Amino acid sequence: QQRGVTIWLTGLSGAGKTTITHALEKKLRDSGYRLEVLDGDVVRTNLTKGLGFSKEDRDTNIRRIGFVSHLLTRNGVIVLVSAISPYAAIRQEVKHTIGDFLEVFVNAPLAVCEERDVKGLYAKARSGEIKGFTGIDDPYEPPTNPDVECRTDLEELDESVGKIWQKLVDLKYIEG
Amino acid sequence: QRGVTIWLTGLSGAGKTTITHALEKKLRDSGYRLEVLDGDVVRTNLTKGLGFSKEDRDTNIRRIGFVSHLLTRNGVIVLVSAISPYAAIRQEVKHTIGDFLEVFVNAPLAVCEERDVKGLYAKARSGEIKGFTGIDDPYEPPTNPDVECRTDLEELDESVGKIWQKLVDLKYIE
Ligand SMILES: Nc1ncnc2c1ncn2[C@@H]1O[C@H](COP(=O)(O)OS(=O)(=O)O)[C@@H](O)[C@H]1O
Ligand SMILES: Nc1ncnc2c1ncn2[C@@H]1O[C@H](COP(=O)(O)OS(=O)(=O)O)[C@@H](O)[C@H]1O
Image (cartoon, rainbow over all chains, first blue to last red):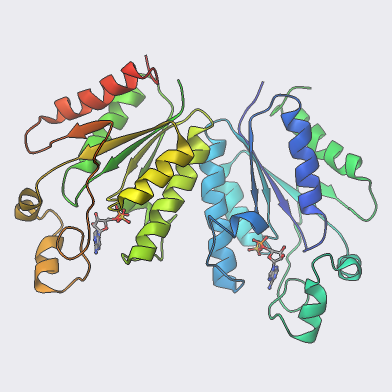
């Protein structure tokens, strides 16, 4: 049994949002659930191609992802969003529009993300090669009341996915 | 019942929006699950910021196709109303979506220009607006649409009826 819902992963670059998204996607698909993934890194090559990382463009980006997530959710689809989405007021705006919405705070310390520097972006932010990088010289406003929080430096992947899954069960979006 | 994109293409003023709304009502009143993506409306949200250059119309149509695809493959009936003047781009979206009906809303340029519903034809003729479809920008008519509605020669009910019957024939609806 399946009801529409947007599962919204927010957090720093490198915090592990994509990894959780993919593991959660697999778990859901293997149970027969109907889903769509909207990953910021990927949709910025199509749906939101042309946008940069100014405040205006991040707002446009998140609002556009929210638009598509809303249409899918209200038609019964489970939508997995993975996007830095650093502005709380914008996340709240999307949550309010969609209603069936779960905010997942993928919470890793800045220092941990910077040490791994998976795509080399932190070093480029520090040197000034890149301007306005989230967490270094651009805001990240952490969720104050997320529905699920995953402290990825302190919990195993299965534990993080498990908490999202259990929340979906508790709220009866998927079968227990 | 089955997902499908119903894609209305045609000149400004040809009657696309009127057919869309009438079709939407008929589908909803029969219990069907749908979404409408009207070019005039999505250009205030989904495609806000784009103009009417070739590259912007391509971006516009491709982005509408992106959303239509995700909805269609999840069982939703999607009604698109957009000038979509480039045949190759309509074909590209049709190919991506698969379950796609191209509806040619075909009114003569002269009929659309004489009504000039939004005053845009007069603005195109004076040069107030540049690159207006059918006046100084292309419209490439479908050569093999799934349904054609000659709105200057058909009653609204007849145009809607043909789209409905096509949906029935192809088993998208009961
Ligand atoms: N200035 C930047 N700030 C954050 N991420 C950036 C920046 N420049 C490039 N990126 C890349 O863009 C990705 C973030 O895109 P989004 O999740 O779509 O951002 S968001 O702020 O608009 O939500 C990061 O994973 C990173 O790879
Ligand atoms: N240069 C223009 N050409 C066509 N339509 C225009 C133009 N400028 C403003 N408009 C308005 O924009 C609408 C067309 O938008 P679309 O259907 O989204 O066009 S499309 O070519 O990109 O598919 C028309 O109904 C008309 O009202």
